[PDB]
Length: 72
Length: 216
Image 1 (cartoon, rainbow over the protein chains, first blue to last red):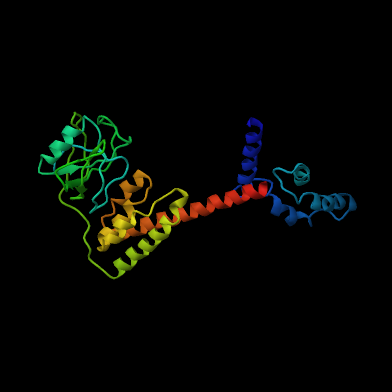
Image 2 (image 1 turned 180 degrees about the horizontal axis):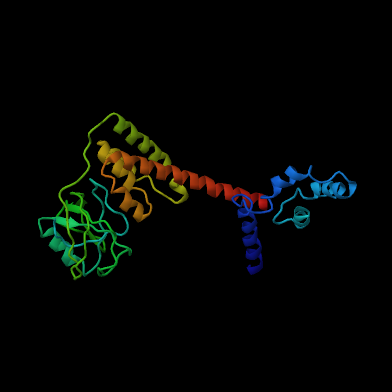
């Protein structure tokens, strides 16, 4: 019960970080699609921007691969 | 200024023209309430910080004192001094001289009286229908509809408004700042805003519960 109340308690932490939580990885979410075009026209940085474009789209507080794609 | 003994109610400051139930069950308060009815039935009901404190203290009372009169000379035996009271007038506080008894200052007679009956009655009826839908909405915190015996038995909007407002529950300091509003219309808009904000907090709880559901 300690383990599963810990799990659901941090799940409500994620949910309050998502609905009423404006300060999260969703804060920079608009800056991402705002600045995908300011990535450079050489293939080296453009390719990695486009491959993080879809890898980021999941939840930025609980999903593991979405946070590294979010920060990157 | 009227100097009267202090008899406490739990956390509900009596609104003007209110006949409220009384729960005074302290052995140190029966003498004070009997002397209050022995003083030509003139009584102060100063709100208390505690639910039911045994003895008054110089730093343990709420900021509003208020004149009241007692409707009946006998007390219903229920473990407390269940006596039928009435809102006689209003009072104020200047300074404490600690006792016991803590002597309290007073005021002249002050209540609410109706001056208009068209716009006032429309606003009272809007708060009344919002109070009906609020009693239907406060079932999340279980508010009964036995309040409809009093908010519908009365007919005068000046007491209809206070019967609507006293039958619900909110913070005591909001009552200290809403009985500063002698005019009834500001009291109407404050109570209606409280009911609407209760609806909004219900919706906010539902929104965060929906986020918990999709987080699942």
